[PDB]
Image 1 (cartoon, rainbow, N blue to C red):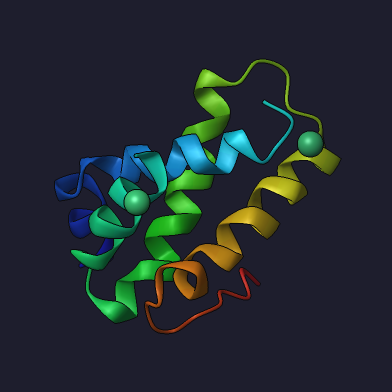
Image 2: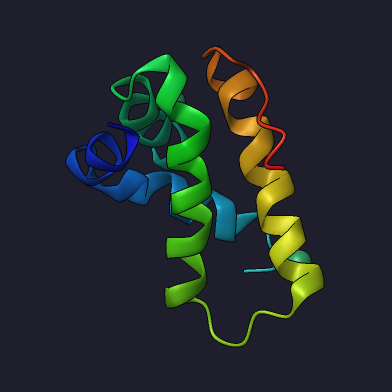
Length: 90
Ligand SMILES: [Cl-]
Ligand SMILES: [Cl-]
């Protein structure tokens, strides 16, 4: 279950940091390894959880900035060369 994989791979904490990095405040390689270790069909679910989790170390996050964080997270599979390359986050 994707929820379990997310917890096991360190809550994708390095990806949380990439997501905030590019959301108005070697990490990417650790992010891609954490995410690689999640099964393909669970990567977008788990990046969704990473976005949620990343807002917690963030202060105030307005909804525009939140949407930005999902936009960042949706490019991370493709950046990492991991299927499914993009997440719709519908
Ligand atoms: Cl931002
Ligand atoms: Cl690297």
